[PDB]
Amino acid sequence: TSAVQQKLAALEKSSGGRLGVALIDTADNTQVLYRGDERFPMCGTSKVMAAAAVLKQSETQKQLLNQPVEIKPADLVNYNPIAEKHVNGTMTLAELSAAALQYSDNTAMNKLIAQLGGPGGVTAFARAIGDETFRLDRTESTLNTAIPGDPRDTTTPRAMAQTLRQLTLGHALGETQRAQLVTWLKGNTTGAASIRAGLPTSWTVGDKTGSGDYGTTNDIAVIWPQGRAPLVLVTYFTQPQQNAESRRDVLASAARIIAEGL
Ligand SMILES: C=C1CS[C@H]([C@@H](C=O)NC(=O)/C(=N/OC(C)(C)C(=O)O)c2csc(N)n2)N=C1C(=O)O
Image 1 (cartoon, protein in one colour):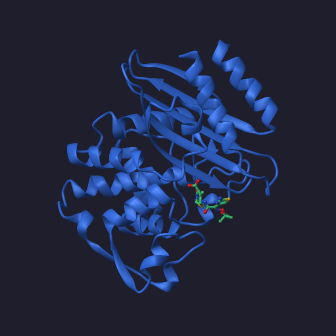
Image 2: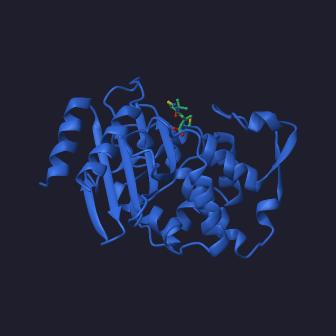
């Protein structure tokens, strides 16, 4: 047990829940893991895989991101802040990707899933880039049920950190696609109280949050400090009570502990 792992264990004990953390330091390719091989419900953090899968399609279909997609009343689900603005109209796949990633729009996510041929098309892209752990089983909004022990719509912190590294810092995507994903993540609007809240305010962050039942509160992030190699940080948190409140503060505290031990 390292110093950082003892503090993360203390944070978890103080929280009442179950915490999963994976850090990759790309300077020396070292890793910090806390419950790094346990499964956690992804919730909206799975939207990165779906957006990346559509970006991968656009490497062959070069104008794909410009393709209009109808938004119909039947498409609306539980949380659709951007798509509701375009019902009975269209959004492009670029606009749907940005809405899914930067506003956590669940209707937008369902349009990405449909473009990929169902949840199996998202999982397929994960396997194609070497992620053997990720599984997407359902569409929105039921993929956020986050039931303890349910393997559906889960991954592990170790696997998600490696995948996020390959998609953003690595070259699992083409050059313009990789840059587009980074731009989208940097422009996220839902992460101010999560990993970002625990990091020095001068560091540049791109991130995607997730939330669900059982007070499931997640965030995955690529971090660019000034003057050193970037980091990839995954923080997953879930709780014993189905109706538990969100705990974004736990993710901020985990990020702060990781930034300390660095
Ligand atoms: C803040 C949101 C808006 S909802 C959107 C999606 C996120 O992962 N979550 C849900 O749709 C969601 N589903 O749960 C229901 C209740 C639909 C379920 O699956 O039964 C949920 C629960 S608490 C919360 N906030 N969002 N996700 C998050 C996020 O952090 O990105």
